[PDB]
Image 1: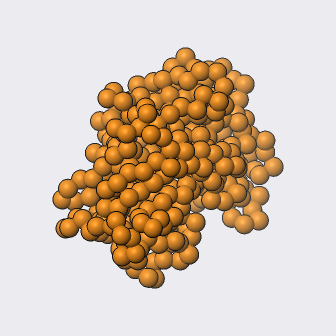
Image 2: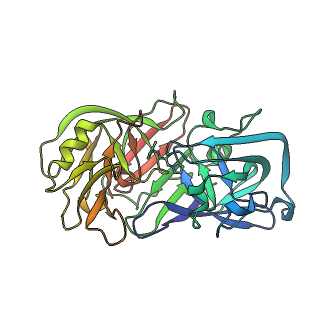
Length: 330
Ligand SMILES: O[C@H](COCc1ccccc1F)CN1CCCC1
């Protein structure tokens, strides 16, 4: 089997991407944030504290003939950015772009933190990291991909995120028309539950490539590119007026600037992020100070290849017995 679904930026800055997902019988379609940095499929639901729902579409398991309460199971998750959610668990039929999994754990939110409430466009998350990170207790549950894997033509999914445009998540096949050149594959460590890999270096604009190992994760659920302070300082030093602002919470730059590209290495291959991808617009409405798309990971504990990086590539998440990651230009 295979599946193919269009993913759409939630706003004009590509702050996140949503993908329609069918849950239950008859289908209830919710728009979920596909997140390769976590491993829970959770949704706003009929059980969510009413005051914490503001515009989201909810899953109502009582209206699904295939929904079953997973007795005694609960979940609670705290993300790297400080947001959180928790609740109970159902199993139900879940379909993405024509690919159907029966008995998928669908985690129903009873509580969500303010940042989720405040984002009316995101009805939940669909985690695509390794199932070892799943928070369901006392019996850990499998991700959608993990459940689908055996049935897929090939045990892979691909992320093809657009810049200010729709893109595609495919399951079970590689669309050879979706990228240019070849796909370069690189090793993955699953020890921390993430799609963790090692970049071979970087360049800033037309500058010389610096060969240096940078360990990090491929995370579709993170908006920006978080890299070591040395790397980030070298990038922003090329932008007149750019500076790190403690008050704003990162590097900012004049909105009048044209930004240089940023290149990262994948083996002997190179992925180039155009400068425009690195512009996240005014820090506040009407400001001429703009927020940078490349930020320091110093406060995080891990480097994160988020959407800023991933949208410059066609990315293969290879879930074979020995997982790997593939990157191609597009
Ligand atoms: O947790 C990710 C972002 O992680 C990186 C990060 C960004 C900013 C501050 C601290 C951090 F760790 C956001 N995702 C959004 C949906 C689930 C998590």
